[PDB]
Each structure stands twice: as structure tokens, then as C-alpha cells.
Length: 48
Length: 49
Image (cartoon, rainbow over all chains, first blue to last red; front, side, top):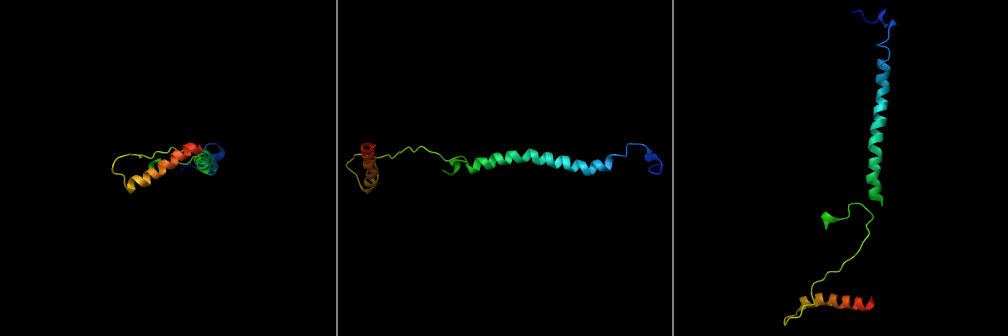
């Protein structure tokens, strides 16, 4: 149990938790950007 | 007709008329009359067209 008291003068831990909160965003924007247009394809098919 | 409805497109058409009759036999009845009474009018649409 050498872990936080002096060891985080280094890197490694550093970015992780930030990216947990950030990566969430990257996924859901991409997922919607996949699904969306091709929903409008089958909506536009109907409308006409 | 159900299997073959235009599954979501702009329902645009042609109409083909297929009425099978104008049959001459000694027996013609009311059956032959309700049919041959379309056939007459198709022949009339020939004049009219």
C-alpha cells in the first residue's frame, strides 16, 4: 500500500477519472450520429 | 392485397381493367347480366376514348 501520499508526483493515475467523465460524451454523440440519418431515411420514405 | 400494398413510397398508379365475361351461351342469367353490364360500358369507353 504505497499508493497516493508521495507517489502521484508521477503521471499514470493523472488522466483517468477525467476521461471516465469525458468518454461518456464521445460515445453517445457517435451512437446518435450513426442511428439518426438512417431513421430519417425511413421517415422520408413514409412522408412522400 | 395486404401483402402487396405499396410499403411507403408515393402511391402512383396505372389501372388495368380485367373483367372476364361477355360469354354467349343459351344460359345467360342475372350473373351474366351484372358482368356483361360492365363490359358494355368498357366498349362504350372504347368509343369515349
